[PDB]
Every structure is written in C-alpha cells, then in structure tokens.
Image 1 (cartoon, rainbow, N blue to C red):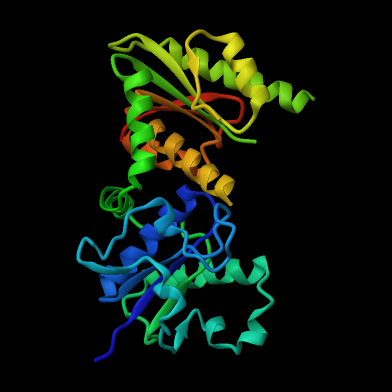
Image 2 (spheres, rainbow, N blue to C red):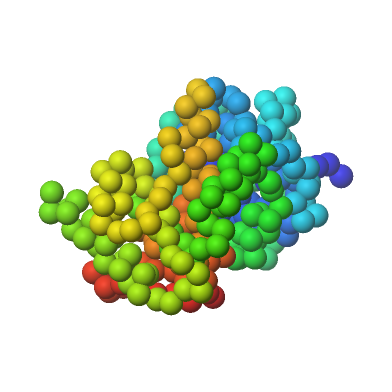
Length: 292
C-alpha cells in the first residue's frame, strides 16, 4: 500500500485559501489521504516557488488525524499519479494554458467527486480552484483551530486587542474595493448606524478594515471611536496585516460585511455573535444575522 494525497493549492486571500484548505482536508480525512498545503505562488510572497504557508503559520504535521505536509518538501517530493482532475495527467507543456474555464471545470469536478460515495482511484487529488462552500462548517472551524499563526503576528494581534478591544464592545467593519463610490460610503454609514443602535454590554468602538485610505478618513470623520491597524518584505507585511485584521474581526461583538460574499470575513462569520450585511436576495436593504 502506498501513500495517497490531496494537494490544496490556493494563492489568493487567506479566507479563500483557508476555506479551500478545509475542503481539501475534509476529502483527505474521508478517504485516508495525506494533505499537502501548497501555497507556492501566493500573492503575498515574491519568490514563486516558496511555499507561503510557513511564512505565516507555524509548522503543522497533523490536523485532526490527517497527516499534513505544509512546507518546502512540495519542491522535493514527487506526488504519485494517476491524478484527479484528469487535466493533471496531461504533459506539462500541455499544462501551460490554464484558463478560468478549466479552473471552473475542476471546481465542478472536485465538487461531484466530494459528493460521490466512491473514493477516486487517482493517487493524488490536485485541488487548484476555489473550494469555498465545498465542505462543512465544522471542517472550516477545525482548520482555524488546528493551525497557528506565527508568533510575530500573534504578538501584534495581542497588543492591538489589549489596546483597543479589551474593556469594549467592538463593531468590526470590512469594506473591500462617483455615484458608485458615494453610494457605497452611504451604505457603509447606514450599516454602521444600524450596528451602533444595538445594545452592547461595554463601551462601543468601531474597528475598520479597509484597503482604502479615503474610506478610512471618511468613516473616521463620520463616527466616533473609529480605529484601524496602522501602517518582498512588503508582500509578507501585506499578508501579515491581512491576517491581523481577519483574526481581530473575529473578536468583535458585531461584524459588518461589505460585501458578505468575501471570504475575508468568513472566520468572523463563524465566531461573531452578530453579522450585518446588505441582502443579496433584497438589494439596498440591510439584514442582521444572529449566530448561528
């Protein structure tokens, strides 16, 4: 009997990477395979063959009974074929073209595979598409509980928690990405107003996570007690600030998701008591979700 694998490849924001990790993990568990975390080519790492996982998380060899390879051994080990999806059996010169069409195909093919009663005969499953929603909520939670941020990142979360969150009830706001820009700011303000009108056991502050300096300035000038985390190595720092925000969001009493399609706030969605978002099914109208 030879070792068999599921490789989780993702290179986008960490919420996407970690959700998609949970999906790969689940299939590995179900089918008795070893999980490979392959974050080579991350948007946060300049060096294209460096596995980014260890740059942000501590080494992990097991997650809930599933053996894990999370490091630069991806550059040394030859994972065995046959491969699923079947595209991965093609010669590498034929694998240079990898358009979105193909990637979406694979998401679909992995989705039916994960739903099928029979394990695949392939020795290695290559997961290299978005696998958000392709696992249980428990699978996602297990991931978050069983990997650990690098201590330098934790130290920063810990300092900011003590400095702003301790003793307070924090409303977290994630805003991602002229009538358009004006409308969005209006909408964010409407959301904050709703969040602020709820009752909290401690004095309220607003924790804003946005990539826009304009939004930070405007939201801060429009509400009291608004704060945000300040400030190759810049890729790493970009990744670290993302994680700091993602994890602090999950310590908030209420979180506003703008938009609620973003995996950035999925972890908050799992942990936070109250979520506020604009309704997909009913546009322009705020809705509130108590957890669950």
